[PDB]
Image (cartoon, rainbow over all chains, first blue to last red; front, side, top):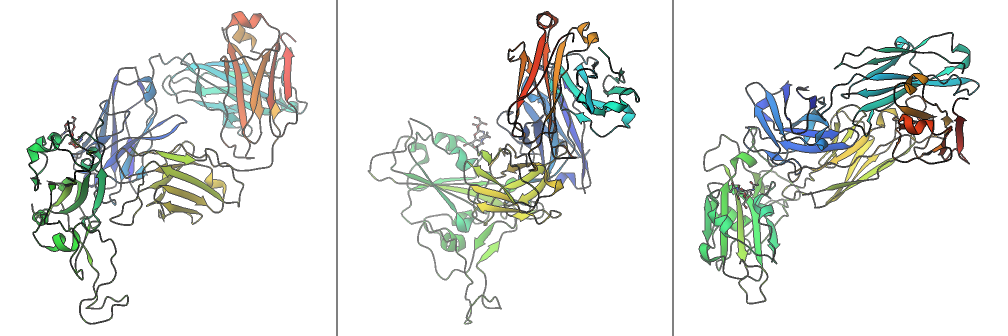
Length: 226
Length: 195
Length: 219
Ligand SMILES: *[C@@H]1O[C@H](CO)[C@@H](O[C@@H]2O[C@H](CO)[C@@H](O)[C@H](O)[C@H]2NC(C)=O)[C@H](O)[C@H]1NC(C)=O
């Protein structure tokens, strides 16, 4: 087993400079090259860099060459990557990833990966999410079940959790992928299906938990006769 | 005209092992050998049939780059004569050679801490090689007088054997990567030659 | 450099059936000094770091069910999944490691093939407190449908809108191997007042003719 944890990252401004560090444990950090692999949300993996086990040779990608600089502190058992002159296309999830020297030459394939960071490139304040109700008591009458939901607008950065009915109601909740609107601000809708015979019997709550703002803003969603 | 790939012959991540040296025909180029000769990265840069400082102004029918990796001690074996194990059983240079030989130390790419055993060189061939002969087939060898029908008992050996290639090796045992250019000075229409 | 093309994009297969993804590299990633074939096959579940499944393009990494198998040589390679189970809904990546820079592939979202499903379609004109907020957000919830393909036409007084329409889809839903979709039309207040009818439409395999859920503002 090897435990690699990627530190650093988060929010940056276009043109800022950031510095990521992977702390590895479980093996001799000075006898294995290391890689970085970027993965922009929903796109797919992409190579970034590589080191040699004595920290001499460093090869990069094509779309990065001359922008990032990847070093490796053996004494602290850490791998550092300094990003310079970030563009809007560099928002992604960054993985460190340990080599396994079996190929004839030094660089070879990668086998053990670490949890990813969340480097996000955009210059906008961490605005608190705004919660809008979508109780279709009188817009979603399907006879048996009504599908009612909750939309969120204008929150940044990425991590957010939506919880319905204190976590008691788990079935029928469709957690949707967050998408940043053309205005540059994220949004998502979470919806549930509820039998029409138990609409007013049980109150319904939309809870948003967003760590950077520590937003724990609840909204009660209740039917309207209209 | 257009440049030609010395880049993918010298900036090569994977160099083939010596018994199966890799050959590449490069042509339709404007070759600048000033880059190679002015680079100090090499340890041996020895041109035989020509003068290394006059290679910019000739024109060649076709130029072939061979590439492999050998021990640092016996990089001497690469010569038009100069008999020896790699020079005879593995890579045979013709006496009438007209080209250049480049070799540079690459201990920091080919030698891994546990030792690199993926590089093999051929030993115990029944006979020598024709000049520029590539022999990738390794059947069981016969050494004594036994019938070597897939056996390996005390007189029926296997021809391939591995180098050590550890970072602790001596200056002579470290790997050296070799690329040798052979020119076709024939008077056919020229295809590759510098400005 | 060497570029990997991995086909297909989606590979939907039902349980017990077989499956095969293929990859083609621009150059030939085949070392010859040994008879090793520098290439590897990873997989990734949604929201997790990837794993290793094949290296040397044929061998298998310890701890992997026999159902996978990598074959091929030269510049053509294939990953064959003999049997399918629940734990094989993942996006698969090819990865050369011959010449730096290394390269990956686009993926293959190996889903689960099921009987065609029936969408359940709803609609919502924005809540009154949002009309005081400054956003004209209307949504149409397409739930529990398969296969993936579904076009959504949002009609405002019989007028398709473009640009101001944002849609998104969930992953392969766990309970029934169906999908969902959160279609929305986001607008300002100015244009919102100028119309009274909205409509969301869809075509699908389980739908002979489009199913429409509309209304008039104010009821
Ligand atoms: C690959 O070998 C080539 C020689 O064929 C070297 O070219 C380098 O290119 C950069 C940019 O001009 C300069 O540093 C020098 O021209 C060369 N650098 C040296 C000799 O250290 C080079 O060694 C290798 N390529 C790269 C990108 O380093």
